[PDB]
Length: 415
Ligand SMILES: O=C(O)Cc1c[nH]c2ccccc12
Image (tube, rainbow, N blue to C red; front, side):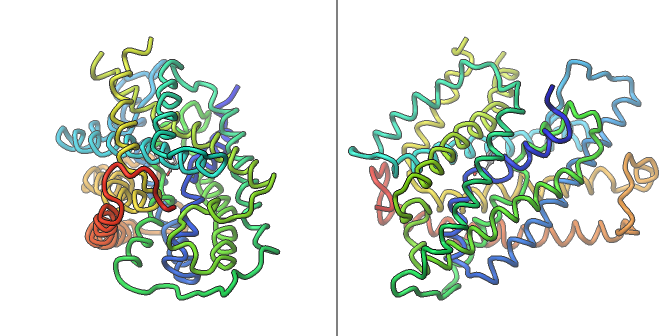
C-alpha cells in the first residue's frame, strides 16, 4: 500500500523537477555560473519555506475543521477549498483561477517539452504535424479515471530522473571544452532577467503539493520530506547544469534543449526515452486536478473531451521551449506559488488570538514570529519586483522577439 512517507518523498522528488532539467543549462548560459548557483540556492530555500507555509496552512485548516465536526473519511481537500475556508469568496475565486490556469499552461509546457524531446530521436517530417500526432496520444489520457497508484510512477520517475541527471553530469567529464569555448555570463538586461525568471519556474511546488501528502499517516511531517526532496534535487541539478554549461560554453543561447547538441549514443537514447516517459506521466499528474475541477464544476471520455482541445491547440500554436517557461514564470508561477500563500498566511493570522491557537508552532531556530513577518514581507516584495514587476518586462519582450523571428504557427523552432 502506497502513500507512505517514503512514497511522499519519492513523489516530491519526481515532481519538483520534471522537464526543467533540460532548460536549466540554457538559463545558466544566460546568467553564469556563480550567479546561477546563488540564485538557485536562494530560490530553493524560498521554495522550501513556501512549501512549509502551505503545509502549515493545510494543517491549521484541518485542525479547525476537526474542531468544527467535519469528517474527511472519503474526501480529499484541494488548495482552493482551503483558500475559500480561510480568506473569503473573491480570494477563493482568485486562487482557483490562478492555480487552474497555471495547471493548464503546465500541461501545455509539458506537451511542448515532450514534442521537443521526441524531435531528436527520429525525425523525417515537419515538427508541427508531429505535435499534431502527439495530440491524440495526449488526449487518450482522458479514459483513465485517475493515477490512483502514484507509488510506481513516483519510483520510476525518481530513478530515471536520477540516472538522466547523473549521465548529463558524467558525459561532460570527457566531452571536453567546446571547440573555441567561450564564457561571458551576463551580457545585458532582457536576457539576464529572462534567465533569472526561468529559474524561478523549477524551484517551487507547482501547485500540486496540497494533495501530494494526503493518505500519509503523519500529515504534519512535510518539512522533512520537502527538505530532503529539495536537497536531492540540488544534488541532481547543480552538478549536471554546471557541467553542461562549462562543457558547451555559449552554445546554449540558441539551442536551449540539452539533447540537441549531445552526441548520439545508446545512453543518450535511453535518457531521452526516460525523459519522454516522465514527461507523459507528469503531464497526466498535472492534468488530473484540472479534470477533477472541470468535472466538479460542469457535473466515459465525453466529460473531459472538451477541455484537452484548447491545450493541444495552444501547444501547437507555440513551439517555444525556454521562452514559454520564462513567460509562465513571470506571469503565472510567480503568483500561484509564492505571493498567494504568503498573502493568505498573513491575512489569516493577522490577529493574535489565531496565533495563540496555532496548529503548529515554528521550530526552535526561528524564536519569534517577527522573523516570519519580515521574511514574508521580503519574499513578497522581491517576487513582485523581479518575478512580476520586471521578470515579465524581459519575458514578454523575448516572446515578441521570438514571434518577430518566427511568427505564429511556426513549423520548426530552434533549427
Ligand atoms: O513540467 C514542468 O515544467 C514542471 C512541473 C512539474 N510538475 C508539474 C505539474 C504541473 C505543471 C508543471 C509541472
